[PDB]
Image (tube, rainbow over all chains, first blue to last red; front, side):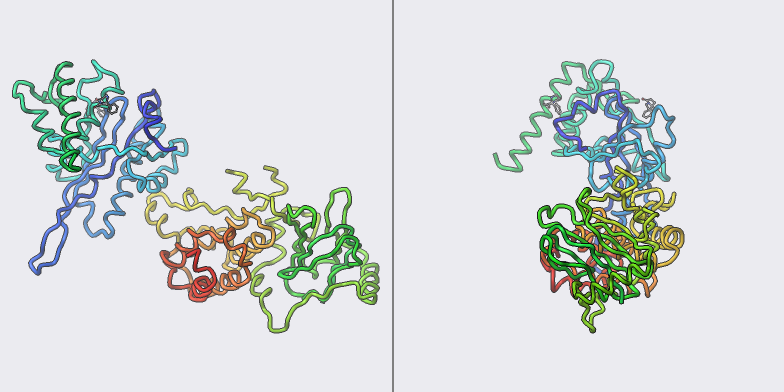
Length: 237
Length: 300
Ligand SMILES: O=C1CC[C@]2(c3ccccc3)NCCCN12
Ligand SMILES: O=C1CC[C@]2(c3ccccc3)NCCCN12
């Protein structure tokens, strides 16, 4: 059924699974026209497809040309997501194909179910969690490759860097969600926390800085802090 | 006009004949139903007084044989049988009419209700849905499940309605996933009408038969089938004009006839609200929308 707190541990077992987030697929800026009406200008987007056990992020960049001449783009975006996820599954060897795909928004369930009718054994599941994957575009290297794309393109990233050398997939995905929740609540503050010390760098082939274990505990506490703060500033507590 | 005699009425029972019904008391001198209009299928149905559980009954067409009802005290129900001896049958019916031991099929002359509910229903198609080839009539009851229900368990006692499934490879052409799921015209017109049903009359016949089994026996799988066939038309952008006009008439008379106290269980809020207000055909069912809004405004 649905994925929730009670079955968070299933994410880190040995059954291959992928999260799919479509929030950033169809992105626009809203602006005024010369006549004073309002119009939208689409910008590049991405599908966020993530194996939570391994950290493998299949980032399919959605170039604005896919919207040209199309109507009802918010609805098309869900079907385009489903088409691209189906194509990715079909491109993988059978032993790498997921047993479950978990969608972060219930509106993806029917589009994905229909595109995957050929795979009756792959379970398509919703979740009760409010996961912060929309903030993926606040990771600078991810945003940069999306915005520079001039054509459709799949780009492969390990979203956990080398963390699995030192920590478990439950602690890694837990850290990723903490960093993304922070970035979603106050991007500037979160990025300040992550980068304030110039001596901790981001390796060319990584997304996040090269923190020691001890530094990660400090960082995590600071992110643990920010999210309560901005909660007080918003809610006045 | 044709007749279905009864051997006797040993148990108290409510007897239905099409949309009519009457109570018969234990061992009352009842010997059947006369003046049944020729040219239509009919259904004779039963609900025992002791056990209102299990409504059951028989679809039949008097042009296909001489039929009678006889209680079976072993199996505990009123059974339809065929009499092959024509002289024996005529003699029996004539004696029962002389002693006036039969009720008359009580059709009012203005009233086209039964025609309007069975316009496309043929006995030959009923017998393909209800498989029991050694009889010319067909038994249905409240509990029989459909072939699609058995896929989601005795195959011989099932209702073999045409399986409709909107999220199936049959419904969805490779590479037209969004198009075919949001506009079911391909599935309606090519798969179902051209491919399986051959014409709209057979489609409407199955739809009408599913409604009637839902209404008379409370058969849940039949209700599911009726709603699915409505939704498939309403969710298609391209439907022939004559089909829409006929669908409006069909549903009008079904809604008109449905028992008011059963609307809560026999009408699916989601399908009806989608069909009348959100679907491609939301503006094409004027008669049906008008009777639905005046009779069941709650459901909507
Ligand atoms: O970790 C790995 C393994 C290979 C991979 C990969 C493959 C698929 C999906 C994400 C990542 N390619 C380059 C990125 C890092 N790589
Ligand atoms: O900030 C915190 C406190 C709770 C949490 C956690 C655990 C599971 C899911 C999300 C967050 N514990 C370990 C990871 C860091 N965490």
